[PDB]
Amino acid sequence: FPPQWICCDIRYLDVSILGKFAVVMADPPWDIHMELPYGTLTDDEMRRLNIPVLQDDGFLFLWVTGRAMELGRECLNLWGYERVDEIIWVKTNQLQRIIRTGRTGHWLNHGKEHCLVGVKGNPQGFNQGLDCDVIVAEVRSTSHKPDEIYGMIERLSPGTRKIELFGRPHNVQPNWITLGNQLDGIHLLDPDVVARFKQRY
Amino acid sequence: NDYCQHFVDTGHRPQNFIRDVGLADRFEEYPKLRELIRLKDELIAKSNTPPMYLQADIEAFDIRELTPKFDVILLEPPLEEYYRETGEKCWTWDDIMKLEIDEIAAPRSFIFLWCGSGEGLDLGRVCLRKWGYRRCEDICWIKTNKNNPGKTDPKAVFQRTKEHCLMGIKGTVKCSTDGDFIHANVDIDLIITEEPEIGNIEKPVEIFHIIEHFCLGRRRLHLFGRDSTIRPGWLTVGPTLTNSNYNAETYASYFSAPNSYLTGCTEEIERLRPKS
């Protein structure tokens, strides 16, 4: 299926209309207890996200930073996953070098972003160990995660439907439904999703 | 350009393509970055204790025999995980948790715990809690395979090409206020070296540099170190050491009056180091 998306608030959308997905990915605006130029979700709001209905067997990719290294582990276990891997995106500059300077963390400088990998139930037809748990990529977009993750997930789970939470316009992909409050309207093509969407809204 | 796809095609890990990761070549073209590191390493060297070391079977050792309290503790317990998965005592996370690290840590202090890349990322956090630390950074040792391209835990979904050294903080430290205990942001939370040979269990020596640059406390303990890791400025404790020169009275005397347990700082390093 071509890309599909729903401009919405993730706290409030009835996600049961969306069906089940082999992969769930979220890059949420964690409350990391610092002043930030964007709005965050409280810890309670994050815990209460209705992730568990999105999936019965499959994987979760949950980007984490700061205190959400621990809160994200708590959410992963709350949502019924076992953490089985941890990917890091190593950020390079235009010349494939680490930017070592500035003050980019509280104690040490930060050269990477982390993504917890969780597994739920008993998934079928995935390809283990094709990719490494280190991504090397320059900062390209206003997104805090690299586009390479989409190819890794496809090679892991080819042809299956997948859902992304807190996605932005440039994140829409084939085989993915993208949810976020900055997308352009609603664009649904799967016949079963449109059906339930009409019934619910 | 997608280095993930390139790894799938050729077996060269994406980290193989990061440039200038060595201790020397990273600041070759950045004289004033290199100067900060040079001056700080000189300050470390000027204030370093001579190497001290104690052979001890840590599982059956009363850790309280190590005095005085430590400003930084580096742990490298040989993980039974590693020897089971690949083929002295090997340690489960229950074994590691039983260590009484909190009995020898200074009231303000840091820990650096090598956790591997599997269950240790979660259980190492539990250990930090038990010993009274908060997880505050995660130093990833990213391993290249430039000399040996290709593929290489049953629960894993991806090939594991790094190890995590979790960093924890104990007590109250304030980066702007406590400039006499820490120099924050001098190093980044990544170490990049070539995969060691199978069975070579050494950790990258750069982890010492990160710790020494970061914390000005001079009381530095390396648990599970070896002959090959003894280092000025450090007390090394482990079962495989072939001699022992540790005397707790002598070791403590290096930090008591007229000395300080802190390195202090020069006016030039204060003018060069990153600050708010």
Image (tube, helix red, strand yellow):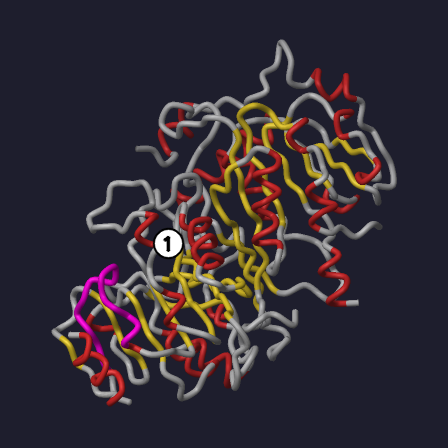
For the point 84% across and 39% down, the residue is B57
Residue A16 belongs to magenta span: yes
Residue B33 belongs to magenta span: no
Residue B17 in the figure: left or right of residue B98? left
Quadrant position of residue B227: top right
**Secondary element type, mark 1:** helix
Residue identified by numbered label 1:
A47
Residue B171: percent from left, percent from top: 50, 27
Residue A166: percent from left, percent from top: 27, 64
For the point 46% across and 72% down, the residue is A59
The reply to whether residue B48 is in sight is no
Residue A163 in the figure: left or right of residue B250? left
Q: Residue furthest front?
A: A199
User: Camera-side residue: B259 or B11?
Assistant: B11
The reply to whether residue A97 is in sight is yes
Label 1: how many Cα within 10 Å (few below 14, some 14–19, many 20+): some
Does residue A40 lie above or below A59 as drawn?
above
Residue B85 in the figure: left or right of residue B156? right
For the point 27% across and 67% down, the residue is A140
**Tag 1 subunit:** A
Q: Residue furthest right?
A: B242
Q: Residue furthest left?
A: A185
Residue A14 in the figure: left or right of residue B99? left
User: Camera-side residue: B80 or A134?
Assistant: B80
Q: Which contiguous range is marked in magenta?
A: A4-17
Amino acid carrying label 1: it is Arg
Residue B93: percent from left, percent from top: 69, 49
